[PDB]
Length: 84
Image (cartoon, rainbow, N blue to C red; front, top):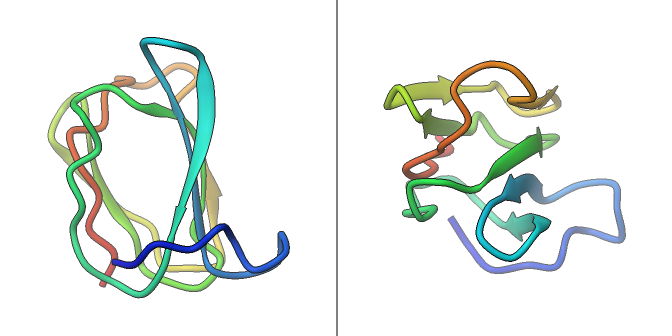
């Protein structure tokens, strides 16, 4: 993974994490696993990496880049990410 404020809104990795304070999309870069906090989801924009985020079910949600998924119903509680 890496730290990057999205690529202008059309690349890099962007994830919508909602918890504690309020909703907020985190944006990193490359592939790898990065602890999320055990509760930080609301949508995901993996448009450049096969991202895997262990949702509340430790459900390694491995999206294969170029994919926007969320958790407005499923178990909302990503324990961490892991793009590969």
